[PDB]
Image: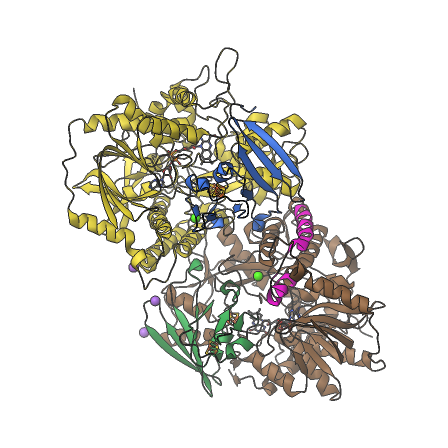
Chain colours: A brown, B green, C yellow, D blue
């Protein structure tokens, strides 16, 4: 194996929406900066944007302000958000939409939000702009841990899955932009269609796990976003009209506010109470309207076309069935992830984060993730100004990470595969930590079982054996998700209230509780190998 | 998920540089192969990359797929989609890259 | 392929509990009768008894009578059972237990020589070799057996059953078995719904995963009437390993508790089998699960006795306890519900039969878990039905002779139907794929585990149409060998059974059996529905048609 | 489910005549093979039948199996069960055929 030491000024882990904009913004600030992206897959399509987008959801119309955005975000989730993070995102949403147009995204008219787009190639256009800016990219390269020196992050380790190479990447500052975590719970269709899900099945919590292993603080893992999407194909609903139950009743009219959480809650009630399935009532649209729908879905979720063809579904005659996904651990549509300051610096010196990997501010969307990448990289650039990558890393520490990364490749005694352990984990979380099978409900006794069962899975990781570097990537996805899952269980155990309906359904503490208007954070103690909960008080945003 | 029609595949390798899951690789004989069809997200990136429509997307029979398929051919300014129903009837849908919805 | 024509007097389909006893009893009545069992697997261990059984659960202990047996069986359905069928079983239960002892089953006895009661209607045994003992007795009676031979359809001359078609999975052979009378003893159906653990552990279930409703499907295709497929028995068993609970509950006298340690059954007036399951579901749904059998505080000797008992009938639990570090004296035993099964032993779904166990088709009798109308049957009740059916079949065949001639075109039609996917070069689906597709449909739209067993009209109407689309795709299946051909026929049969289940569930607009038949849009029991819902398959329309049969008081 | 330890299997075929699912067959070289381990019901009929204990039952990892195994030796009047836990610790339990429980 060839061990390669690389040096860069700014290292970005993950070349998705936030990481691409961070790298572009860095080059725009200083052409001379060395900027390197380490990307698990292929930057042209990597991350949540691979299939395309339905729309640009987050920007401000005339007369709307960051304050308007903060209030929307609180209405779409709860009052317990990091207002400072939401406000500073809000200030740049419109600027980020303008950059997407500059990069080549097709946009047309019919306020400002009334635009027509083709989001099919949003990721390629973002990737092309990144490479045109002079950013260096290591594709098909999996990050596995931060390089720490005296409690300061000064790089990261990674291994290639196409070459026999292990990378020691020294950097003056590191930006985590790996996205959130899927695959902790069972998906809607385990087995044959186990990766038909809403979030990317290839964002498996690496950023969360590297952060936890390195000592960084996470926040609000008990808030698990669940998507309400077209059944089985998990396609967007925005494209597609009102919500109806199987009796044809517009059941949302029974509730005062029609918010994203409410639409999911209401749909679950209808099904549980015997009036499902629930649907988007497309009946009565025109033949041309059907053709428009087909063309739009081909540009961002083509599987639904195959479902319609197979099941003889014409949306003008048959409404579109919807249902909820597995719970995800995300800081884009949810508010789970790294705990950061207003400059997107994590709790570790030298490490910043942006996007779905950052907690505290739900309803970020593409523009919000792009904006966070800019904020983070601007802070990192100011931080690296004085220093230089002269940190010397002891060969023993390098060898230790190598041993950890490649352990199952040299495990002749192993008896389990990553896929077997992944399914075992998903079963534990689905059954004892509030998955689909429990209609997302959690209670203390089951959570305590989940805690103990996850520890037994962790013990069996040393019995995993892999045959190649691709299966080695899968092993690390499982290692990372087990740690994230252990944190999720501790967060769910700790918050003895129900703050977010569906996303955090503590059936044994069903009421909201004013005594719990505070943030629940976690830290991983490498000495005791236990997750430790930290309370952080809520702070009104008052910049002076 | 997707299938590679090896008789149509010309071994160009293009589909192996797009997948967000790293699922596609070029075998020694030049043909593309998917590591595990169960891990496909149906993002269609590979389908659109193939210049000879040797990659087709279909819904897993286990979740109700009946054999309908989706193929895609990229032009200088559009994507031409070929949708074949479960009885073999083909519908051709061209979506211009500049077309907005 | 070898097409083998065989002639027999009595043909028995399925060499399980009912089939074995039917065959033995036939040879008792007339040793010169040619009796032949067609068995899908290996008779030594085939069927629900393969792993052993925990006890004999239908036995009239001292003070108990056939009349009191009926009174107890009646309770769960609020009296809607076939009392004639239950009573005639009750009159033979103790005889069947004595037969098992004569065949060699170890049955515990007290100093007086009486069987040792375990519960009101059960007795203690070592049941590990119950099926080998039954099979040995069958072969020693001179009964002929075709093992590894799959029955696919009855032979019908006009509306009279006069044999059956079957294929071997070990030889390139197809059987045309002419019989004076046929007795269907194939057991019920599992694998219609999704199991507790799809995929890697998909056959970890309570009922035999190899009883896939062939008897129901053969009967439906031949024109016979089925009954009460809307009553889908669901087992409350040890979680994941699906092990018996009676050994812990009845044997140790332990209570059901929630995760708070509360004996939640005390909140309910009646502690019946369906209510034990319903109450467990409620506890979990309301955030007080998991639920358990409280073994805490038993002795080390009791733990050892439990391990030996479970090794003798459900060994998987020992592995779970070792892997998860469960000692029952310190940690209670977690319990949960299974998939719904279509069975006439623990439930009351199956063929509609007269008191002599004749189906609605002349020449065809049925016995055991394949027969509806009488729950709480168990192994002795199934044996009893085998005897009743064969006694009537023997009286019926007394007049006739195997002079019926089948037309060669009819044989050719069944051969083409049976071997179609083996010759389907253009096929594109496997039996496994279609099986998973069907289980998903039923789980999501016909009240499987994922909906907590609840059904509503709208979902069932969807299930009806989705099952029809699966049937359309059966012609797109290909198989590569005779073993996979058997799996194809398991799917074909289960699709037809599932279509019937859906129609029955749609038709009964009330909730009579909690859990087993939860019509949430008609949540109350309704005296206007005190009647049997039956079905037949219309081959001209390819549809299931519902028939109502009135309840008739039984007076002996 | 079950696994066949091929190095121990002597190719006798006995395990191929008991399974209620027809899951076990003899290959060209005589050793036993299971058609699909996912279809096993864990009835243990094959485990008991094998005279050299080349068949061991174990719980699928996907449902929480950690490596404990069960083997069984039939005697003239008993079954001798060999239970090995996930750390290799062995417990042997004989259950006499004529012994009844409780
Ligand atoms: C199906 C779907 C549809 C959506 N549609 C819309 C829409 O219409 N409009 C809208 O505004 N928003 C939409 N969103 C939201 C938006 O896509 C996400 O919030 C945003 O893409 C997240 O950006 P990110 O940079 O945090 O993560 P990503 O864009 O997912 O990027 C994360 C990157 O990290 C990489 N990575 C992961 N692990 C590692 C590792 N170990 N080493 C190296 N790299 C790694 C990944 O490969 C990826 O390139 C959608 C999201 C989804 C899932
Ligand atoms: C797990 C379990 C534990 C039980 N424990 C007890 C207990 O402790 N006490 C008690 O009293 N009762 C018990 N029972 C109930 C009792 O075992 C059943 O009620 C009884 O065995 C059913 O008998 P049967 O003849 O109808 O079906 P089975 O005994 O299952 O026999 C059906 C036969 O049909 C064969 N067959 C299926 N399809 C075909 C085909 N196409 N062609 C040919 N043959 C076919 C099968 O291979 C099998 O040999 C238990 C049942 C189960 C499932
Ligand atoms: S459709 Fe997307 S996830 Fe699936 S193989 Fe192609 S590129 Fe990969
Ligand atoms: S892009 Fe198409 S032709 Fe080229 S290797 Fe892939 S499947 Fe084959
Ligand atoms: S344990 Fe039972 S079901 Fe499994 S292979 Fe052995 S005999 Fe067959
Ligand atoms: S019984 Fe045992 S030794 Fe004989 S073939 Fe089967 S596994 Fe091999
Ligand atoms: Ca996965
Ligand atoms: Ca099956
Ligand atoms: Na029209
Ligand atoms: Na087709
Ligand atoms: Na057809």
Task: Give the side of residue B5 with respect to residue A51, left or right.
Answer: left
- The residue at the far top in this view is C112
Residue occupying the point 62% across, 56% down: A501
Please identify the quadrant where the C terminus of chain A is shown.
bottom right
Q: Position of residue A441 (x, y in %)?
A: 60, 50
Task: Give the side of residue B26 with respect to residue A64, left or right.
Answer: left
Q: What range of the chain is rendered magenta?
A: A449-476
Task: Decide whether the magenta segment is chiefly helix, strand or loop.
Answer: helix
Q: How many marks?
A: 0
Residue C476's place in the image compared with B43, above or below, is above
Q: Is residue C38 visible in this depiction of the protein?
A: yes
Q: Position of residue A91 (x, y in %)?
A: 70, 78
| Viewer-closest of C68 and A58 | C68
| Viewer-closest of C111 and A260 | C111
- Picture quadrant where residue C102 is located: top left
- Picture quadrant where residue C426 is located: bottom left
Verify whether residue A467 appears in magenta.
yes
Q: Is residue C523 visible in this depiction of the protein?
A: no
| Viewer-closest of A266 and C504 | C504
| Viewer-closest of A358 and D10 | D10
Verify whether residue C366 appears in magenta.
no
Task: Give the side of residue C545 with respect to residue C187, left or right.
Answer: left
Q: Position of residue C334 (x, y in %)?
A: 60, 39
Residue occupying the point 63% across, 78% down: A60
Residue A188's place in the image compared with A294, above or below, is above
Residue B76's place in the image compared with A75, above or below, is below
């Amino acid at each position: 194996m060839d061990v390669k030491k690389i040096f860069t000024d700014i290292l970005i882990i993950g070349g998705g929406a936030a990481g691409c904009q961070a790298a572009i913004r860095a080059k725009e600030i200083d052409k001379n900066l060395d900027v390197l992206i380490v990307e698990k897959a292929n930057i042209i399509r990597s991350g949540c944007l691979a299939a395309g987008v339905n729309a640009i959801n987050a920007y401000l119309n005339e007369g709307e302000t960051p304050e308007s955005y903060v209030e929307y975000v609180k209405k779409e989730s709860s009052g317990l958000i990091r207002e400072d993070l939401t406000y500073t995102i809000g200030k740049r949403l419109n600027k980020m939409a303008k950059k997407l147009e500059e990069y080549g995204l097709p946009i047309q008219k019919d306020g400002k939000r009334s635009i027509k787009i083709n989001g099919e190639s949003i990721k390629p256009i973002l990737a092309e702009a990144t490479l045109k800016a002079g950013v260096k990219v290591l594709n098909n390269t999996i990050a596995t841990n931060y390089i720490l020196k005296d409690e300061t992050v000064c790089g990261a380790y990674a291994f290639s899955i196409k070459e026999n190479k292990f990378y020691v990447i020294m950097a003056k500052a590191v930006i985590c932009t790996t996205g959130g975590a899927s695959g902790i719970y069972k998906p809607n269709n385990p087995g044959a269609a186990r990766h038909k899900m809403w979030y990317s099945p290839f964002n498996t919590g690496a950023g969360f796990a590297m952060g936890l292993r390195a000592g960084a603080e996470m926040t609000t893992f008990e808030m698990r976003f669940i998507a309400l999407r077209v059944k089985d194909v998990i396609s967007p609903t925005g494209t597609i009209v009102s919500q109806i139950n199987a009796l044809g009743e517009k059941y949302m009219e029974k509730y005062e506010n029609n918010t994203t959480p409410m639409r999911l809650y209401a749909t679950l009630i209808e099904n549980l109470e015997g009036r499902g399935p629930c649907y988007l009532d497309t009946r009565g649209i025109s033949d041309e309207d059907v053709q428009k729908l087909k063309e739009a879905y081909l540009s961002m979720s083509p599987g639904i076309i195959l479902k319609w063809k197979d099941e003889k579904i014409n949306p003008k005659n048959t409404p579109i069935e919807i249902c909820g996904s597995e719970p995800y651990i995300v800081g884009g549509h949810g508010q789970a992830g790294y705990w950061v300051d207003i400059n997107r610096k994590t709790t570790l010196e030298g490490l910043y984060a942006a996007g779905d990997v950052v907690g505290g501010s739900p309803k970020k969307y593409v523009t919000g993730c792009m904006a966070e990448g800019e904020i983070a990289v601007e802070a990192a650039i100011e931080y690296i100004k004085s220093m230089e990558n002269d940190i010397e890393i002891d060969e023993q520490e390098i060898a230790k990470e190598i041993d950890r990364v490649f352990y199952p490749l040299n495990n002749k005694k192993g008896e389990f595969s990553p896929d077997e352990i992944e399914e075992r984990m998903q079963k534990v979380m689905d059954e004892y930590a509030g998955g689909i099978s429990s209609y997302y409900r959690v209670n203390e006794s089951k959570l305590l079982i989940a805690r103990e069962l996850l520890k037994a899975i962790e013990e069996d990781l040393s019995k995993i054996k892999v045959r190649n570097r691709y299966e080695l990537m899968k092993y690390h996805e499982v290692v990372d998700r087990i740690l994230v899952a252990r944190a999720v269980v501790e967060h769910l155990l700790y918050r003895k209230e129900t703050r977010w309906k569906c996303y955090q359904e503590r059936v044994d503490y069903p009421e909201i509780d004013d005594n719990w208007f505070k943030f629940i954070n976690s830290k991983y103690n490498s000495q005791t190998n236990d997750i430790e909960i930290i309370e952080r008080e809520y702070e009104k945003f008052n910049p002076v | 998920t997707i299938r590679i029609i090896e008789e149509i595949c010309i071994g160009c390798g293009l589909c192996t540089k797009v997948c967000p899951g790293n699922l596609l690789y070029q075998r020694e004989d030049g043909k593309s192969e998917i590591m595990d069809k169960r891990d496909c997200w149906d993002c269609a990136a590979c389908v659109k990359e193939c210049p000879v429509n040797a990659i087709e997307m279909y819904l897993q029979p286990e979740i109700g797929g009946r054999g309908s398929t989706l193929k895609a051919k990229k032009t200088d300014d559009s994507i031409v989609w070929i949708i074949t129903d479960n009885n073999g009837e083909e519908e051709v849908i061209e979506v211009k890259n500049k077309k907005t919805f």
